Image: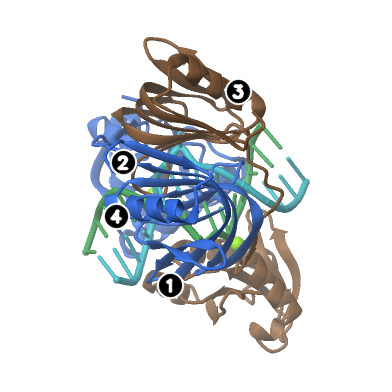
Chain colours: A brown, B blue, C green, D cyan
Amino acid sequence: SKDKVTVITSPSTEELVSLVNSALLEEAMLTIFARCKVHYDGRAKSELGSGDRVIIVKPDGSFLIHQSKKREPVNWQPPGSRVRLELRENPVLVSIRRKPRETLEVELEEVYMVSVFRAEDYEELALTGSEAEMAELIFENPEVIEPGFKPLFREKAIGTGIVAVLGRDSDGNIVVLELKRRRAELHAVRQLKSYVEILREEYGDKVRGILVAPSLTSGAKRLLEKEGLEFRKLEPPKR
Amino acid sequence: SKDKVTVITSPSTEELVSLVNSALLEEAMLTIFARCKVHYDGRAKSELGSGDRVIIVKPDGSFLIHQSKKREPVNWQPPGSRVRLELRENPVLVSIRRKPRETLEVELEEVYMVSVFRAEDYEELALTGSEAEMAELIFENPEVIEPGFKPLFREKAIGTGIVAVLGRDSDGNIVVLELKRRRAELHAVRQLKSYVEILREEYGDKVRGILVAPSLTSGAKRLLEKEGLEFRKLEPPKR
DNA sequence: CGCTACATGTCGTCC
DNA sequence: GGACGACTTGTAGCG
Ligand SMILES: [Mg+2]
Ligand SMILES: [Mg+2]
């Protein structure tokens, strides 16, 4: 029980309970391969008929059921649920949460494998090419937006909404930027347009919105043009 | 290669290679508990240092690296990626994707366990309490909105944007509905306000927007009132 | 906790 | 294929 991994194929009920319960109390990762039915009631409600899936219960409460396809678990519960194995006509893995109140029930018809992974990880993801990274590049070197641009505020509350960057231009105007790290879609324009209508109300018609992004969709460009907003092409930088 | 599950703890290199290549070829699920490093370059860029993780490869090319916390894999590749094992100074799992170009590299420093799960699942999820379900309700029972409300279109392309439900009211006004399955946000009122604007362009002052959802955030309420749009509290049905 | 907006979002789905 | 919007979205950042 200090070995990183413990594994049992075609486990007996005793062995199942032993590992399942040990991992939950040991703050370790539980992985299971089983034919199962799944029952979810919570924010929404779902039923999943009998079939083979991979099941993961992380020490933080995260509960995953993965089918042989997609990138998303077919069913899940997010970090913070309380999980318990429950012996019934079949074993039943049960995830409970109270805000919001949600129940996830996994019923194990046949467990092919149960396993305990006592995983030691002190390390964190270091990612670049984000919106945050664009915002940094614009404050270090405002030249990328345009000559004379002076950035002032990052993630600024206005009365309704939060603007990514608020600044001033060489004509002394108020400028709003909305940044997108990938091709900007319609809703980016709605955001930007919303912010700009709001500030025009205090500061006048001279306020400029600019959408900053590596490209636009057609609809983006269309609404951006209909509304008299602007576009500066900027790629998110990779450190 | 017949049994539903194969497990080899502390595999050797030939064992590792043998199992991984069987997995991929057989359209089984590959599961590896391992100490690894992860290198990602693609839409964005990252480096994950040495640590214990659960790696999954699904037969449709989904590639997941899970740490012992949260619901999201720390690194991942969506379906369609092409996976393979390469023998470098360490064995290295490699995920390539074209359109967009992405590389995901998982360097296996030490593999505690490796497993192949030849998994059979023919059943899909059946979910209720969605936005679709709300819309079906409104079409079966429009009086849930208001008496003398006639629905016409669902998920209808307006000039710019797609409206959720479009119809008329008893007084000859045009009615846009924006539906939400949970408490509505600023995002929701911006959507509504956009649609209502684009439709006033044509049919004039005869357009009403109605935001339909179980509740509203403060800001969404604030903004709703300001631009003079309306609200019907409605919960999605669970059937 | 509630609000706001990003994400390597992923995923269905209308033209 | 490109555009567009939902999702049990999850997740961080702030107040
Ligand atoms: Mg923003
Ligand atoms: Mg909508």
The lab-note entry on whether marks 2 and 3 share a chain reads no
Q: How many neighbours does mark 1 have within 10 angstroms: few (below 14), some (14-19), or many (20 or more)?
A: few
Q: Give the residue at mark 1.
A: B101
SS label for mark 3: helix
Give the x, y percent position of residue A97: 56, 25
| Circles 4 and 2: CB atoms closer than 8 Å | no
Query: Which residue type does callout 4 highlight?
Result: Leu
Image position of A107 with respect to A176: above or below: above
Q: Which quarter is ligand 1 in?
A: bottom right
Q: Is mark 2 within 8 Å of ligand 2?
A: no
- Residue in view at x 34 percent, y 56 percent: B162
Q: Give the residue at mark 3.
A: A22
> Which quadrant of the figure contains the C terminus of chain A?
bottom right
Q: Give the residue at mark 2.
A: B118
In the displayed structure image, the side of residue B133 where residue A205 appears, left or right: right
- N-terminal of the pair, mark 4 or mark 2, is 4
Taking depth in this image into account, of B205 and A178 the one nearest to the observer is: A178
Mark 4 belongs to chain:
B
SS label for mark 4: helix
Query: Which residue type does callout 2 highlight?
Result: Arg
Q: Give the residue at mark 4.
A: B25
Taking depth in this image into account, of B196 and A58 the one nearest to the observer is: A58
Query: Which residue type does callout 1 highlight?
Result: Arg
SS label for mark 2: loop
Which image quadrant for residue B141?
top left
- N-terminal of the pair, mark 4 or mark 1, is 4
Which image quadrant for residue A235?
bottom right
The lab-note entry on whether marks 3 and 4 share a chain reads no
On residue A4, which mark appears?
Answer: none
Give the x, y percent position of residue B98: 38, 71
Mark 3 belongs to chain:
A
